[PDB]
Image: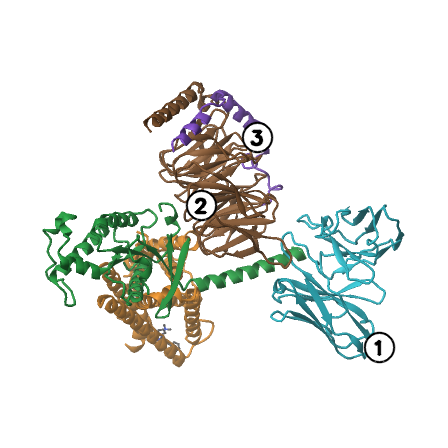
Amino acid sequence: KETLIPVFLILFIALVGLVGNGFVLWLLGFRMRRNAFSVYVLSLAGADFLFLCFQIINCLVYLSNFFCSISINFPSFFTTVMTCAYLAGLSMLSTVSTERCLSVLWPIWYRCRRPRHLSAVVCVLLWALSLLLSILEGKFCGFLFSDGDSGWCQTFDFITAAWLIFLFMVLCGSSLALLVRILCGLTRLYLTILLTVLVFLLCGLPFGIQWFLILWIWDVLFCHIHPVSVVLSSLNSSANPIIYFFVGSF
Amino acid sequence: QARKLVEQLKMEANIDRIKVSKAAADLMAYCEAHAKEDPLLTPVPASENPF
Amino acid sequence: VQLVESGGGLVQPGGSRKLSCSASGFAFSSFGMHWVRQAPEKGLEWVAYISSGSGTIYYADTVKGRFTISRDDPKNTLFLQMTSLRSEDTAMYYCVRSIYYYGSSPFDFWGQGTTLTVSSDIVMTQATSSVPVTPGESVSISCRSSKSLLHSNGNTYLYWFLQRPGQSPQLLIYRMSNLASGVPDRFSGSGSGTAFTLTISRLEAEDVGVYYCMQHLEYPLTFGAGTKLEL
Amino acid sequence: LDQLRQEAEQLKNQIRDARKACADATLSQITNNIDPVGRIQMRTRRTLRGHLAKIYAMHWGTDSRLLVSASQDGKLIIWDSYTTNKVHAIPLRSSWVMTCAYAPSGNYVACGGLDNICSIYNLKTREGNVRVSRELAGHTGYLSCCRFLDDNQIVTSSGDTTCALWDIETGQQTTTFTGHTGDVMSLSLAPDTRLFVSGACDASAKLWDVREGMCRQTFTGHESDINAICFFPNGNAFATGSDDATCRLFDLRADQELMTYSHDNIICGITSVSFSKSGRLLLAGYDDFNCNVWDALKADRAGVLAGHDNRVSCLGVTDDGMAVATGSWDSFLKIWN
Amino acid sequence: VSAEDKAAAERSKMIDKNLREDGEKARRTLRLLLLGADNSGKSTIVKGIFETKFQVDKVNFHMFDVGRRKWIQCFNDVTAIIFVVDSSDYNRLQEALNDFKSIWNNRWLRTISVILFLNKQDLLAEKVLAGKSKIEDYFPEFARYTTPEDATPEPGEDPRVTRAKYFIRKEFVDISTASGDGRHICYPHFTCAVDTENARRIFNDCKDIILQMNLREYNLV
Ligand SMILES: CN(C)[C@@H]1CCN(c2cc(-c3ccccc3)nc3ccnn23)C1
């Protein structure tokens, strides 16, 4: 009963986010053309949309079952789908950073000798791996129709945390290499790179770390750290499209 | 030389001219005669468009 | 243009044989090729089909599972492989070229033939079987079909061929109204659905033989029986 | 030379005075008491994909089903409009093309460009392929337009300030048409094929005779280059579009200008111009990526055609008036109805 | 669909396949347009249309010259324009500068870069060490110009030749940067008739052009 403000902030942020996601979907799906940068933006916008809708639905269940006596129960398939969206949305950012680094480092190869469908190929493959790990965790920890076991849940959670740290390492390394190469050879891109790394760190990793490691290793924690984390993750997902598409179009 | 220009202008300054009113009336009459034969002006139904 | 065929000869029942056809004179890789056979005294029957790019193959139901078709584009050859030969396979075999696009004229060139002796469907009929004619007259020939040959797009798929004594057949009319290249303007053809006629004006010698009509609306391809003109 | 220059000035003055005593009314007031047209909404019915570069020219065939298109990738394609099938694809010796044509009988096509030759391609023949029939050399500048009169005659315009008529079998020029001061950019033939008009970069258009080889009239009202030109279906008027951002209508029997088509928002150029089967609508293509439909008797806009992502370079109307075709620098073609 | 219509569709599909193969082959090569004047030494650099092909470091090039307000629109999607100038005929420098200004401000060429080649520099050295001709009788402002202080590179030549070279470089570059909005750049160079290192400068400059193009799409710059 000391969490109404957190839920209201979540509701407002999500309302702001879905509009931008939908407009981006409409423009890049029907109106505009598609280069190798637009494919990744479209996939990221889809993942963001899904995540924000499920945050909305959990907000609504909470407000209804509290402000009114009537309460409802939603199946756990939903938590698994939220996990899949979160992971895919984080992996598309690392893919974009690597593609930028390659374009600067080897420009003629990127412009002249590259397959024309590598973007779609990579998007599908990353979605597939994300969904595989999401379901495998959903079953072996009890969120699906079964009773869980301890070892399987712990093993899957720890490997997912390792995967997230790997994504951060890739982001940092590629951005470093780009910036070094541009120096040894000018303000707008410094701002772009710093903004990207900082926003990823301080608005994407909190929820993942808290949900997959901390509650295992370390009730004075959960009830005070879960909502702040979900707030910040919603903010990241809603602010991504302005950073990647609208500023691109003036 | 310039004799070419003067010979050309001499051949081009002596022809028969009719007034603007008659030419405008003729074009308008042509437009009114064939009005029921242009599909892009009067649309065709879906049973006779090849496209 | 030329098409020359080889193989042939006596074959014991149950044996095997391979027929080969070699082309010279045209762009072979953009044509689709058929095989058509003729009995010792009967009409013409269709056998198989291979497409440009080798992406489609069709067989008549009488030879499925025993015969196979293939082509070798760089050396310009067409093959047909026998297996489990019977006594109804005594015939003389032909090779035919055909090209498909808007305004085209399929079944243009027919090669000569090789002989081989071994020791539902749209049925369409030619009631007339013999007509005696004299030079300087006009004559009409009819064949009618079982189902209508007028597709929605407006084309009536019907073809007319002529076979002179001791020769290979040639094309006269394609799609019921059009006149082939090299054919004198005295031939003509018209008709409605399920009724077709061919009219010859100022008939001459070197215009006698047997006339066939074919349909090209759906596989298998089906021929008539044959009307012949005698002096 | 002073005497000759004075005579020339006097003659121009006499022409200008005689073409004023023959103007008593205006097309604007002769056509005031008629009902207008309405709003012409047209929708895309086909999109024809397959080119990988800019599109410069297109031409319809007389059967109203087939068309040919020229591209900077170095290829010509014959399309089937009803089904969007491809009938042929002809490789080119040069990739710098600026014109193409389709013969009235349907047996030949032509193309030419920045290499100073007009090539004729034989379409239907034995052997199954499409091969070159004749190459015509003799121009000293790039080719801009070519049109077929028959199966053995063709008219070409070039950037060396001249036009020529050819005999294909012999391969030689028959008549040379001279008189322009700058490059010639377009030409259009009359229905009876005994006259044609040419538009140039000296801001003038001339009307020629084909058999005699002379020049009968010259029309001067624009103030920059003329890029497109076309007859009225009647055979007694033509329309011209310029980089001035205006179109004009001229008459041959009164020898002057009747109407102008301008609007204060347009500041771009005009690339192509065509009429409709009735002579009531005028189609024009612009550099601002879209196309406009004008009323040819009241100087009013009747509609727009907005579907292209780059410059609109070519335009065309079918003989039976069922469709219009546009091609653009974004490598697509469209059919509207 | 009838039998013949299906056959027609299959033929159309094969035509598309060949078209795509040809396009992918054509994507590798890079195209250049060679402008210049007479007495520019234009035909001896990389030691209707006269074409020319060459490759450096496993990349293909394709160079065109035509022997202009109208046909210049065709060359709207080329990688670069190569402009060549004789830097010894002082009577005809102003023509070259005006020509460069015209080709720099064209409507259809607002995103195409230019590689300059100030050719015939040995004759310039001889004419500036001779003393029988004065650069300042044609451009008055040569009397009051001095070499940039800390940006004077040279391999062991005179100071006077350096002043004469840098003045002409400046004239062209300061036409270039007057009004270009930063969307296309000019790369200047000095060459003679015996220089063999001329196919490498084009390669480096083209690599830079493509780097800028890649940056603009990804919104980095
Ligand atoms: C996000 N993952 C899926 C959550 C994080 C917390 N968590 C968890 C699970 C279990 C458990 C062990 C065996 C069988 C069923 C459940 N026990 C504990 C004790 C403290 N946390 N916890 C799972």
What is the letter of the purple chain?
A: B
Give the residue type at disc 3.
Ala
Q: Quadrant of ligand 1?
A: bottom left
Chain E, colour shown = green
Q: Is residue A237 visible?
A: no
Give the residue type at disc 2.
Ser
Identify the image quadrant of residue E166.
bottom left
What is the letter of the brown chain?
A: D
Measured in 3D between alpha carbons, the distance from the residue under mark 1 to the one under mark 2, in whole angstroms, is 71 Å
Quarter of the image for the N terminus of chain A: give it.
Answer: bottom left
Q: Is residue A148 visible?
A: yes
> Marks 1 and 3: which is nearer the front?
1
Chain A, colour shown = orange
Helix, strand or loop at mark 2: strand
Q: Which mark is residue C119?
A: 1
Give the residue type at disc 1.
Ser
Horizontal relation, residue E90 to residue D18: left or right: left
Callout count:
3
Residue in the picture at 75% in, 78% down: C16
> Marks 2 and 3: which is nearer the front?
2
Horizontal relation, residue C169 to residue D169: left or right: right
What is the letter of the cyan chain?
A: C
Q: Which mark is residue E211?
A: none
Measured in 3D between alpha carbons, the distance from the residue under mark 1 to the one under mark 3, in whole angstroms, is 76 Å
Location of residue E45 in the rendering, given as x and y in whole percent from the top left corner: 31, 62
Query: Which residue is identified by label 2?
Result: D313
Identify the image quadrant of residue E195.
bottom left
